[PDB]
Image (cartoon, rainbow over all chains, first blue to last red):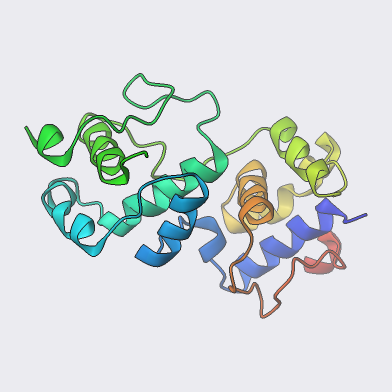
Length: 101
Length: 100
């Protein structure tokens, strides 16, 4: 069996020696995001879509692709009892134009 | 089909209204970590193990359970071509005392 204690000790050694990526959020590319988006029957995201979300990205300071990595995560790991704006589900009934209002 | 553009717009709405959790890390319970660990044939982590790692946690400034969440994430989503200390796999040949 894999000794978890050791693996954790090793990760700590990695950090002591300079590693940081596995501690931060990963981000993603449009293409990688879509590979995931498709496993869960989500409409593929186009470059246009990405560019169309710029207003909201400028208003929040959160790069669009960074928000995509967040969605990617929720899709793979779930919300785990946590909600978003009080919802237990990811809402898709509101458009960009809707939210910007 | 689920409109991705709309879902992303919603998350931004959520951020605009104060949401943050889905942007930052996700710490973990020793229990939740173990449910995940066993899924991948890893030794379950005990409270002793956690406490034994305190020296390294103090030297790095990153809590044990936070490192556990990091591991949890690596096991569920993989390393994706990225490496750790040059290795392409999660090494478990070194004990806490080997690292110290």
